[PDB]
Length: 535
Ligand SMILES: Nc1ncnc2c1ncn2[C@@H]1O[C@H](COP(=O)(O)O)[C@@H](O)[C@H]1O
Image (cartoon, rainbow, N blue to C red):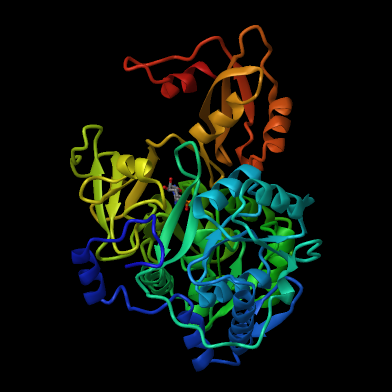
Protein backbone atom coordinates (compact mmCIF):
# COMPACT_ATOMS: atom_id res chain seq x y z
CA UNK A 1 0.00 0.00 0.00
CA UNK A 2 1.38 3.37 -1.12
CA UNK A 3 0.30 7.00 -0.78
CA UNK A 4 0.61 7.35 -4.57
CA UNK A 5 -0.62 5.28 -7.47
CA UNK A 6 0.81 5.29 -10.98
CA UNK A 7 4.35 4.08 -10.29
CA UNK A 8 6.13 0.72 -10.24
CA UNK A 9 7.67 -0.38 -6.91
CA UNK A 10 10.69 -2.66 -6.72
CA UNK A 11 9.99 -6.41 -6.43
CA UNK A 12 9.99 -7.45 -2.78
CA UNK A 13 13.11 -9.61 -3.18
CA UNK A 14 15.15 -6.58 -4.31
CA UNK A 15 13.78 -4.31 -1.60
CA UNK A 16 14.78 -6.86 1.05
CA UNK A 17 18.37 -6.96 -0.22
CA UNK A 18 18.68 -3.17 -0.41
CA UNK A 19 17.33 -2.84 3.12
CA UNK A 20 19.65 -5.60 4.30
CA UNK A 21 22.65 -4.04 2.54
CA UNK A 22 22.04 -0.74 4.38
CA UNK A 23 21.16 1.23 1.22
CA UNK A 24 17.52 1.83 2.19
CA UNK A 25 17.77 3.12 5.75
CA UNK A 26 14.07 3.77 6.33
CA UNK A 27 14.12 7.54 6.88
CA UNK A 28 12.02 10.19 5.12
CA UNK A 29 13.98 12.52 2.87
CA UNK A 30 13.34 15.54 5.09
CA UNK A 31 15.14 13.82 7.99
CA UNK A 32 18.57 14.67 6.56
CA UNK A 33 17.83 18.28 7.49
CA UNK A 34 16.14 17.45 10.82
CA UNK A 35 19.09 15.25 11.89
CA UNK A 36 21.76 17.75 10.84
CA UNK A 37 20.02 20.70 12.53
CA UNK A 38 19.90 18.58 15.70
CA UNK A 39 23.62 17.83 15.60
CA UNK A 40 24.87 21.17 14.24
CA UNK A 41 22.11 23.76 14.71
CA UNK A 42 24.37 26.81 14.51
CA UNK A 43 26.42 25.89 11.42
CA UNK A 44 25.84 27.99 8.29
CA UNK A 45 23.63 25.84 6.06
CA UNK A 46 22.78 28.14 3.18
CA UNK A 47 24.06 31.38 1.61
CA UNK A 48 22.30 33.19 -1.23
CA UNK A 49 23.87 35.41 -3.88
CA UNK A 50 23.29 38.64 -1.93
CA UNK A 51 25.30 37.33 1.04
CA UNK A 52 22.37 36.51 3.34
CA UNK A 53 22.87 33.26 5.24
CA UNK A 54 20.90 30.85 7.43
CA UNK A 55 21.91 28.32 10.04
CA UNK A 56 20.74 24.72 10.03
CA UNK A 57 18.43 25.51 12.95
CA UNK A 58 16.93 28.47 11.08
CA UNK A 59 16.40 26.41 7.90
CA UNK A 60 14.82 23.61 9.93
CA UNK A 61 12.44 25.96 11.77
CA UNK A 62 11.39 27.83 8.62
CA UNK A 63 10.66 24.55 6.83
CA UNK A 64 8.42 23.66 9.79
CA UNK A 65 6.58 26.98 9.61
CA UNK A 66 6.05 26.76 5.87
CA UNK A 67 4.86 23.16 6.18
CA UNK A 68 2.30 24.32 8.73
CA UNK A 69 1.29 27.11 6.35
CA UNK A 70 0.97 24.66 3.47
CA UNK A 71 -1.42 22.54 5.53
CA UNK A 72 -3.54 25.59 6.34
CA UNK A 73 -3.99 25.98 2.57
CA UNK A 74 -5.04 22.34 2.19
CA UNK A 75 -1.78 21.20 0.59
CA UNK A 76 -0.25 18.00 1.88
CA UNK A 77 -0.67 14.26 2.36
CA UNK A 78 0.09 13.03 -1.14
CA UNK A 79 -0.79 16.15 -3.15
CA UNK A 80 1.50 16.80 -6.10
CA UNK A 81 2.91 20.34 -6.34
CA UNK A 82 4.71 21.70 -9.40
CA UNK A 83 7.71 23.77 -8.29
CA UNK A 84 9.36 26.14 -10.77
CA UNK A 85 11.84 28.29 -8.84
CA UNK A 86 15.29 29.80 -9.39
CA UNK A 87 18.45 29.33 -7.29
CA UNK A 88 17.14 31.12 -4.21
CA UNK A 89 16.68 30.25 -0.55
CA UNK A 90 12.94 30.15 -1.28
CA UNK A 91 13.35 26.88 -3.19
CA UNK A 92 15.31 25.24 -0.37
CA UNK A 93 12.87 26.05 2.44
CA UNK A 94 9.89 25.12 0.25
CA UNK A 95 11.43 21.76 -0.73
CA UNK A 96 11.59 20.58 2.88
CA UNK A 97 8.30 22.23 3.84
CA UNK A 98 6.55 20.34 1.04
CA UNK A 99 8.19 17.09 2.21
CA UNK A 100 7.14 17.66 5.81
CA UNK A 101 3.58 18.50 4.78
CA UNK A 102 3.36 15.14 3.01
CA UNK A 103 3.20 16.73 -0.44
CA UNK A 104 5.20 15.43 -3.39
CA UNK A 105 7.28 18.09 -5.21
CA UNK A 106 7.21 17.91 -9.01
CA UNK A 107 10.43 19.68 -9.93
CA UNK A 108 10.52 21.74 -13.13
CA UNK A 109 13.11 24.10 -14.46
CA UNK A 110 12.74 27.89 -14.84
CA UNK A 111 13.14 27.53 -18.63
CA UNK A 112 10.03 25.37 -18.94
CA UNK A 113 6.98 26.92 -20.52
CA UNK A 114 3.29 26.21 -21.06
CA UNK A 115 3.57 22.90 -22.88
CA UNK A 116 5.89 21.32 -20.31
CA UNK A 117 4.11 22.80 -17.29
CA UNK A 118 0.60 21.88 -18.43
CA UNK A 119 1.62 18.32 -19.28
CA UNK A 120 3.32 17.60 -15.97
CA UNK A 121 0.60 19.36 -13.95
CA UNK A 122 -2.00 17.36 -15.87
CA UNK A 123 -0.10 14.06 -15.54
CA UNK A 124 0.56 14.55 -11.83
CA UNK A 125 -2.93 15.81 -11.05
CA UNK A 126 -1.17 18.72 -9.39
CA UNK A 127 -3.15 20.84 -6.93
CA UNK A 128 -0.65 23.67 -6.58
CA UNK A 129 1.98 25.48 -8.63
CA UNK A 130 4.88 27.49 -7.22
CA UNK A 131 6.49 30.19 -9.37
CA UNK A 132 8.56 33.35 -9.26
CA UNK A 133 6.89 36.54 -10.38
CA UNK A 134 9.35 37.68 -13.09
CA UNK A 135 12.54 35.78 -13.96
CA UNK A 136 14.96 36.47 -16.83
CA UNK A 137 12.36 38.80 -18.35
CA UNK A 138 9.53 36.25 -18.29
CA UNK A 139 6.38 36.74 -16.22
CA UNK A 140 5.67 33.26 -14.84
CA UNK A 141 2.39 34.51 -13.36
CA UNK A 142 1.00 34.72 -16.88
CA UNK A 143 2.12 31.12 -17.35
CA UNK A 144 0.41 30.16 -14.09
CA UNK A 145 -2.84 31.64 -15.40
CA UNK A 146 -2.61 29.64 -18.61
CA UNK A 147 -1.81 26.54 -16.54
CA UNK A 148 -4.86 26.98 -14.30
CA UNK A 149 -6.96 27.42 -17.44
CA UNK A 150 -5.83 24.06 -18.83
CA UNK A 151 -5.51 22.17 -15.53
CA UNK A 152 -8.57 22.62 -13.29
CA UNK A 153 -6.94 20.63 -10.47
CA UNK A 154 -4.54 23.52 -9.70
CA UNK A 155 -6.20 25.27 -6.76
CA UNK A 156 -3.29 27.32 -5.45
CA UNK A 157 -0.52 29.33 -7.04
CA UNK A 158 2.27 30.42 -4.70
CA UNK A 159 4.45 33.26 -5.98
CA UNK A 160 7.98 33.98 -4.76
CA UNK A 161 7.52 37.71 -5.20
CA UNK A 162 4.59 39.98 -6.06
CA UNK A 163 1.79 37.43 -5.95
CA UNK A 164 -0.80 39.50 -7.90
CA UNK A 165 -4.15 37.73 -7.43
CA UNK A 166 -2.39 34.56 -6.15
CA UNK A 167 -0.73 33.59 -2.84
CA UNK A 168 2.61 35.02 -1.75
CA UNK A 169 5.01 32.22 -0.86
CA UNK A 170 6.23 34.33 2.07
CA UNK A 171 2.75 34.38 3.61
CA UNK A 172 2.68 30.56 3.66
CA UNK A 173 3.77 30.51 7.30
CA UNK A 174 2.18 29.28 10.53
CA UNK A 175 2.99 27.94 13.96
CA UNK A 176 4.58 24.47 13.59
CA UNK A 177 2.19 21.55 14.03
CA UNK A 178 2.72 17.80 14.63
CA UNK A 179 2.97 16.18 11.20
CA UNK A 180 3.29 12.44 10.64
CA UNK A 181 6.24 11.04 8.74
CA UNK A 182 5.79 9.47 5.31
CA UNK A 183 6.56 5.86 4.64
CA UNK A 184 10.18 5.84 3.38
CA UNK A 185 9.20 3.39 0.65
CA UNK A 186 6.71 5.90 -0.75
CA UNK A 187 7.46 8.32 -3.59
CA UNK A 188 9.22 11.41 -2.20
CA UNK A 189 9.39 13.53 -5.35
CA UNK A 190 8.85 13.44 -9.12
CA UNK A 191 11.72 14.49 -11.41
CA UNK A 192 11.56 15.47 -15.05
CA UNK A 193 13.24 13.51 -17.77
CA UNK A 194 13.75 15.17 -21.12
CA UNK A 195 12.62 11.82 -22.38
CA UNK A 196 12.33 10.26 -25.79
CA UNK A 197 8.57 10.22 -26.45
CA UNK A 198 5.96 12.78 -27.44
CA UNK A 199 5.49 14.16 -23.90
CA UNK A 200 7.88 14.68 -20.96
CA UNK A 201 8.02 11.85 -18.45
CA UNK A 202 7.94 11.95 -14.66
CA UNK A 203 10.45 9.94 -12.60
CA UNK A 204 9.26 8.77 -9.16
CA UNK A 205 12.05 8.76 -6.58
CA UNK A 206 11.32 7.28 -3.14
CA UNK A 207 12.62 8.51 0.22
CA UNK A 208 14.81 5.44 0.62
CA UNK A 209 16.35 5.46 -2.84
CA UNK A 210 16.89 9.23 -3.03
CA UNK A 211 18.42 9.38 0.45
CA UNK A 212 20.79 6.61 -0.69
CA UNK A 213 21.59 8.51 -3.89
CA UNK A 214 22.49 11.53 -1.73
CA UNK A 215 24.34 9.62 1.01
CA UNK A 216 26.39 7.37 -1.27
CA UNK A 217 27.28 10.24 -3.63
CA UNK A 218 28.40 12.37 -0.70
CA UNK A 219 30.71 9.55 0.41
CA UNK A 220 32.23 9.04 -3.06
CA UNK A 221 32.79 12.79 -3.59
CA UNK A 222 34.23 13.37 -0.12
CA UNK A 223 31.53 15.82 0.91
CA UNK A 224 31.93 16.81 4.56
CA UNK A 225 31.12 19.57 7.04
CA UNK A 226 34.01 21.57 5.53
CA UNK A 227 32.46 21.38 2.05
CA UNK A 228 31.21 24.64 0.53
CA UNK A 229 29.11 23.67 -2.47
CA UNK A 230 28.15 26.21 -5.13
CA UNK A 231 24.83 25.51 -6.86
CA UNK A 232 25.49 26.56 -10.46
CA UNK A 233 22.97 24.36 -12.26
CA UNK A 234 19.26 24.81 -11.42
CA UNK A 235 18.51 23.64 -7.88
CA UNK A 236 15.81 21.37 -9.37
CA UNK A 237 18.29 19.55 -11.63
CA UNK A 238 19.13 16.10 -10.22
CA UNK A 239 22.89 16.76 -10.59
CA UNK A 240 22.85 19.91 -8.45
CA UNK A 241 20.15 18.60 -6.10
CA UNK A 242 21.42 15.17 -5.21
CA UNK A 243 24.66 14.01 -6.95
CA UNK A 244 25.61 14.93 -4.18
CA UNK A 245 24.33 18.43 -4.79
CA UNK A 246 22.84 20.61 -2.10
CA UNK A 247 21.06 17.72 -0.37
CA UNK A 248 24.40 15.96 0.16
CA UNK A 249 25.96 19.17 1.43
CA UNK A 250 23.16 19.68 3.95
CA UNK A 251 23.17 15.99 4.95
CA UNK A 252 26.87 16.14 5.90
CA UNK A 253 26.65 19.63 7.42
CA UNK A 254 28.49 21.70 4.82
CA UNK A 255 27.50 25.07 3.34
CA UNK A 256 25.32 25.50 0.25
CA UNK A 257 25.97 28.67 -1.79
CA UNK A 258 23.42 29.65 -4.44
CA UNK A 259 24.70 31.13 -7.73
CA UNK A 260 22.16 33.04 -9.84
CA UNK A 261 23.87 32.18 -13.14
CA UNK A 262 26.87 30.10 -14.23
CA UNK A 263 28.60 33.14 -15.73
CA UNK A 264 32.14 33.78 -14.44
CA UNK A 265 30.94 37.20 -13.35
CA UNK A 266 28.57 35.57 -10.86
CA UNK A 267 30.27 32.25 -10.11
CA UNK A 268 33.90 33.38 -9.76
CA UNK A 269 32.91 36.12 -7.30
CA UNK A 270 30.99 33.66 -5.11
CA UNK A 271 33.84 31.12 -5.21
CA UNK A 272 36.27 33.74 -3.93
CA UNK A 273 33.77 35.36 -1.56
CA UNK A 274 32.47 32.16 0.06
CA UNK A 275 35.58 29.95 -0.44
CA UNK A 276 33.66 27.38 -2.47
CA UNK A 277 35.30 23.94 -2.40
CA UNK A 278 33.02 21.99 -4.77
CA UNK A 279 30.64 22.58 -7.67
CA UNK A 280 29.03 20.79 -10.63
CA UNK A 281 28.70 22.03 -14.23
CA UNK A 282 27.85 20.85 -17.75
CA UNK A 283 30.70 20.77 -20.33
CA UNK A 284 29.80 24.09 -22.05
CA UNK A 285 30.14 25.92 -18.71
CA UNK A 286 33.39 24.04 -17.99
CA UNK A 287 34.82 25.26 -21.30
CA UNK A 288 33.71 28.81 -20.47
CA UNK A 289 35.33 28.76 -17.02
CA UNK A 290 38.47 27.18 -18.47
CA UNK A 291 38.63 30.08 -20.93
CA UNK A 292 37.65 32.85 -18.50
CA UNK A 293 40.46 32.27 -15.98
CA UNK A 294 42.87 33.79 -18.49
CA UNK A 295 41.11 37.16 -18.20
CA UNK A 296 39.37 37.02 -14.81
CA UNK A 297 41.23 38.00 -11.66
CA UNK A 298 39.10 36.13 -9.08
CA UNK A 299 40.91 33.96 -6.53
CA UNK A 300 39.54 30.45 -7.18
CA UNK A 301 42.13 28.68 -5.00
CA UNK A 302 39.55 27.31 -2.54
CA UNK A 303 38.14 25.03 -5.26
CA UNK A 304 38.95 21.38 -4.65
CA UNK A 305 36.39 19.53 -6.79
CA UNK A 306 34.83 20.25 -10.19
CA UNK A 307 32.12 17.79 -11.24
CA UNK A 308 31.34 17.83 -14.97
CA UNK A 309 28.38 15.92 -16.35
CA UNK A 310 25.18 15.98 -18.35
CA UNK A 311 27.10 15.37 -21.56
CA UNK A 312 30.56 14.00 -22.24
CA UNK A 313 33.58 16.15 -21.37
CA UNK A 314 36.32 15.87 -23.97
CA UNK A 315 39.70 14.42 -23.01
CA UNK A 316 41.55 17.59 -24.05
CA UNK A 317 39.65 20.11 -21.86
CA UNK A 318 39.49 17.50 -19.08
CA UNK A 319 43.28 17.47 -18.97
CA UNK A 320 43.16 21.30 -18.63
CA UNK A 321 41.13 21.35 -15.42
CA UNK A 322 44.02 20.97 -12.97
CA UNK A 323 46.40 23.44 -14.73
CA UNK A 324 43.76 26.11 -15.37
CA UNK A 325 41.41 25.81 -12.38
CA UNK A 326 43.69 24.21 -9.78
CA UNK A 327 41.23 21.52 -8.70
CA UNK A 328 40.37 17.86 -9.17
CA UNK A 329 38.03 16.93 -12.01
CA UNK A 330 35.29 14.34 -11.50
CA UNK A 331 33.37 13.09 -14.52
CA UNK A 332 29.76 12.22 -13.74
CA UNK A 333 27.71 10.13 -16.17
CA UNK A 334 24.33 9.98 -14.46
CA UNK A 335 20.63 10.32 -15.09
CA UNK A 336 17.53 11.46 -13.27
CA UNK A 337 16.20 7.93 -13.85
CA UNK A 338 18.86 6.65 -11.42
CA UNK A 339 22.26 5.15 -12.23
CA UNK A 340 25.24 7.34 -11.43
CA UNK A 341 28.75 6.71 -12.66
CA UNK A 342 31.56 8.65 -10.98
CA UNK A 343 35.26 8.79 -11.51
CA UNK A 344 36.86 8.46 -8.11
CA UNK A 345 38.72 11.41 -6.63
CA UNK A 346 42.02 9.50 -6.50
CA UNK A 347 41.56 7.62 -9.77
CA UNK A 348 44.68 7.91 -11.92
CA UNK A 349 44.51 11.06 -14.00
CA UNK A 350 44.30 8.86 -17.13
CA UNK A 351 40.91 7.55 -16.00
CA UNK A 352 39.60 10.96 -14.92
CA UNK A 353 40.53 12.32 -18.37
CA UNK A 354 39.43 9.41 -20.56
CA UNK A 355 36.40 7.83 -18.83
CA UNK A 356 32.97 8.76 -17.51
CA UNK A 357 33.36 6.87 -14.23
CA UNK A 358 32.10 3.63 -12.74
CA UNK A 359 28.82 2.89 -10.96
CA UNK A 360 28.04 4.38 -7.57
CA UNK A 361 26.60 1.26 -5.88
CA UNK A 362 27.99 -2.27 -5.46
CA UNK A 363 24.48 -3.35 -6.47
CA UNK A 364 24.19 -1.22 -9.58
CA UNK A 365 23.82 -3.88 -12.28
CA UNK A 366 25.10 -3.12 -15.77
CA UNK A 367 24.38 -4.82 -19.08
CA UNK A 368 25.72 -3.74 -22.47
CA UNK A 369 23.74 -5.30 -25.31
CA UNK A 370 23.75 -5.29 -29.08
CA UNK A 371 20.78 -4.60 -31.34
CA UNK A 372 19.46 -8.14 -30.77
CA UNK A 373 19.40 -7.55 -27.00
CA UNK A 374 22.40 -9.87 -26.61
CA UNK A 375 25.32 -9.05 -24.33
CA UNK A 376 28.36 -7.75 -26.19
CA UNK A 377 31.87 -9.14 -26.01
CA UNK A 378 33.88 -7.46 -23.23
CA UNK A 379 34.94 -3.95 -24.20
CA UNK A 380 32.66 -3.73 -27.25
CA UNK A 381 30.22 -0.84 -27.76
CA UNK A 382 26.53 -1.43 -27.08
CA UNK A 383 23.49 -0.02 -25.36
CA UNK A 384 23.65 0.36 -21.59
CA UNK A 385 20.89 -1.30 -19.54
CA UNK A 386 20.90 -0.89 -15.79
CA UNK A 387 19.10 -2.01 -12.63
CA UNK A 388 19.85 -1.02 -9.05
CA UNK A 389 18.79 0.38 -5.68
CA UNK A 390 18.03 3.92 -6.92
CA UNK A 391 17.11 3.31 -10.58
CA UNK A 392 13.40 3.33 -11.35
CA UNK A 393 11.35 0.32 -12.47
CA UNK A 394 8.93 2.58 -14.34
CA UNK A 395 7.99 6.15 -15.19
CA UNK A 396 5.10 7.73 -13.32
CA UNK A 397 1.75 7.04 -15.03
CA UNK A 398 3.37 5.99 -18.32
CA UNK A 399 2.45 2.33 -18.85
CA UNK A 400 2.90 2.27 -22.63
CA UNK A 401 6.35 3.82 -22.45
CA UNK A 402 7.18 1.55 -19.50
CA UNK A 403 6.38 -1.51 -21.63
CA UNK A 404 8.91 -0.25 -24.21
CA UNK A 405 11.64 1.08 -21.93
CA UNK A 406 12.17 -1.64 -19.28
CA UNK A 407 13.03 -5.27 -19.90
CA UNK A 408 10.91 -8.09 -18.50
CA UNK A 409 13.39 -8.52 -15.62
CA UNK A 410 13.37 -4.80 -14.84
CA UNK A 411 16.43 -3.43 -16.63
CA UNK A 412 16.04 0.23 -17.61
CA UNK A 413 17.16 0.89 -21.20
CA UNK A 414 19.24 4.07 -20.93
CA UNK A 415 19.58 4.67 -24.66
CA UNK A 416 23.27 5.45 -24.18
CA UNK A 417 25.98 3.60 -26.11
CA UNK A 418 28.99 2.69 -23.94
CA UNK A 419 32.09 0.54 -23.55
CA UNK A 420 33.07 -0.98 -20.20
CA UNK A 421 36.78 -1.06 -19.52
CA UNK A 422 38.62 -3.82 -17.61
CA UNK A 423 38.62 -1.65 -14.46
CA UNK A 424 34.84 -1.22 -14.60
CA UNK A 425 34.94 2.38 -15.85
CA UNK A 426 32.60 3.36 -18.69
CA UNK A 427 33.32 5.36 -21.83
CA UNK A 428 30.26 7.01 -23.38
CA UNK A 429 30.40 6.40 -27.12
CA UNK A 430 27.11 7.75 -28.47
CA UNK A 431 23.37 7.36 -28.22
CA UNK A 432 20.66 5.01 -29.43
CA UNK A 433 17.76 7.08 -28.11
CA UNK A 434 16.09 9.71 -30.31
CA UNK A 435 16.95 12.60 -28.00
CA UNK A 436 19.28 15.52 -28.72
CA UNK A 437 21.74 16.48 -25.96
CA UNK A 438 22.24 20.23 -26.48
CA UNK A 439 24.84 21.35 -23.96
CA UNK A 440 23.37 19.01 -21.35
CA UNK A 441 19.78 20.01 -22.18
CA UNK A 442 17.72 17.06 -23.44
CA UNK A 443 15.38 17.46 -26.41
CA UNK A 444 12.95 14.67 -27.12
CA UNK A 445 12.87 14.68 -30.91
CA UNK A 446 9.36 13.25 -31.11
CA UNK A 447 7.97 15.92 -28.76
CA UNK A 448 9.61 18.73 -30.74
CA UNK A 449 8.48 17.21 -34.06
CA UNK A 450 4.85 17.19 -32.93
CA UNK A 451 5.12 20.87 -31.94
CA UNK A 452 6.66 21.80 -35.29
CA UNK A 453 4.12 19.84 -37.36
CA UNK A 454 1.44 21.96 -35.69
CA UNK A 455 2.76 24.91 -37.68
CA UNK A 456 0.45 25.42 -40.70
CA UNK A 457 3.26 25.43 -43.26
CA UNK A 458 4.57 22.07 -41.99
CA UNK A 459 3.34 18.64 -43.05
CA UNK A 460 6.10 16.43 -41.64
CA UNK A 461 9.08 17.11 -39.41
CA UNK A 462 12.20 15.12 -38.51
CA UNK A 463 14.48 16.56 -35.84
CA UNK A 464 18.15 15.53 -36.17
CA UNK A 465 21.20 16.25 -34.04
CA UNK A 466 24.25 17.97 -35.48
CA UNK A 467 27.69 17.71 -33.85
CA UNK A 468 28.91 20.91 -32.20
CA UNK A 469 32.39 21.46 -30.81
CA UNK A 470 31.33 23.36 -27.68
CA UNK A 471 27.72 22.27 -27.16
CA UNK A 472 28.05 18.65 -28.29
CA UNK A 473 24.86 18.68 -30.36
CA UNK A 474 22.70 21.35 -31.95
CA UNK A 475 19.16 20.83 -33.21
CA UNK A 476 18.24 20.67 -36.90
CA UNK A 477 14.58 20.62 -37.92
CA UNK A 478 14.07 18.86 -41.26
CA UNK A 479 10.72 19.90 -42.72
CA UNK A 480 8.36 18.71 -45.42
CA UNK A 481 6.14 21.72 -46.25
CA UNK A 482 2.39 21.57 -46.09
CA UNK A 483 1.04 20.95 -49.60
CA UNK A 484 1.15 24.16 -51.63
CA UNK A 485 2.42 26.15 -48.65
CA UNK A 486 5.78 27.58 -47.69
CA UNK A 487 7.46 26.17 -44.61
CA UNK A 488 8.67 28.69 -42.00
CA UNK A 489 12.27 29.81 -41.67
CA UNK A 490 14.24 29.45 -38.42
CA UNK A 491 13.18 32.72 -36.76
CA UNK A 492 9.50 32.37 -37.66
CA UNK A 493 9.42 28.77 -36.46
CA UNK A 494 11.17 29.85 -33.26
CA UNK A 495 8.50 32.48 -32.62
CA UNK A 496 5.72 29.98 -33.34
CA UNK A 497 7.22 27.48 -30.89
CA UNK A 498 7.78 30.05 -28.14
CA UNK A 499 4.16 31.24 -28.29
CA UNK A 500 3.09 27.59 -28.18
CA UNK A 501 4.94 27.34 -24.85
CA UNK A 502 8.00 25.31 -25.85
CA UNK A 503 11.09 25.79 -23.66
CA UNK A 504 13.76 27.90 -25.31
CA UNK A 505 16.52 25.27 -25.35
CA UNK A 506 14.32 23.13 -27.62
CA UNK A 507 14.11 25.72 -30.43
CA UNK A 508 15.85 24.42 -33.59
CA UNK A 509 19.21 25.93 -34.39
CA UNK A 510 18.69 25.28 -38.11
CA UNK A 511 15.87 24.44 -40.52
CA UNK A 512 16.26 22.33 -43.67
CA UNK A 513 13.39 21.96 -46.13
CA UNK A 514 12.95 18.91 -48.37
CA UNK A 515 10.14 17.11 -50.15
CA UNK A 516 10.55 13.69 -48.50
CA UNK A 517 12.46 11.98 -45.69
CA UNK A 518 14.85 9.06 -46.18
CA UNK A 519 13.17 5.93 -44.86
CA UNK A 520 14.58 2.54 -43.94
CA UNK A 521 13.06 -0.73 -44.98
CA UNK A 522 10.43 -1.14 -42.20
CA UNK A 523 9.47 2.43 -43.03
CA UNK A 524 10.75 4.60 -40.18
CA UNK A 525 12.50 7.85 -41.03
CA UNK A 526 16.23 7.23 -41.42
CA UNK A 527 17.83 9.76 -39.09
CA UNK A 528 21.34 8.40 -39.59
CA UNK A 529 20.87 9.27 -43.26
CA UNK A 530 19.34 12.68 -42.48
CA UNK A 531 22.51 13.39 -40.51
CA UNK A 532 24.34 12.70 -43.77
CA UNK A 533 21.88 14.38 -46.15
CA UNK A 534 21.73 17.55 -44.06
CA UNK A 535 25.18 19.11 -43.94
N1 LIG B 1 29.05 12.55 -18.22
C1 LIG B 1 28.19 12.29 -19.22
N2 LIG B 1 28.63 11.98 -20.46
C2 LIG B 1 27.79 11.73 -21.48
N3 LIG B 1 26.46 11.74 -21.34
C3 LIG B 1 25.89 12.02 -20.15
C4 LIG B 1 26.73 12.32 -18.99
N4 LIG B 1 25.92 12.57 -17.95
C5 LIG B 1 24.65 12.44 -18.41
N5 LIG B 1 24.64 12.10 -19.71
C6 LIG B 1 23.45 11.94 -20.56
O1 LIG B 1 22.35 12.50 -19.90
C7 LIG B 1 21.29 11.52 -19.80
C8 LIG B 1 20.48 11.81 -18.57
O2 LIG B 1 20.50 13.20 -18.28
P1 LIG B 1 19.61 13.84 -17.13
O3 LIG B 1 18.42 12.93 -17.01
O4 LIG B 1 19.31 15.20 -17.71
O5 LIG B 1 20.52 13.89 -15.92
C9 LIG B 1 22.03 10.20 -19.85
O6 LIG B 1 21.21 9.11 -20.18
C10 LIG B 1 23.11 10.49 -20.88
O7 LIG B 1 22.55 10.48 -22.18
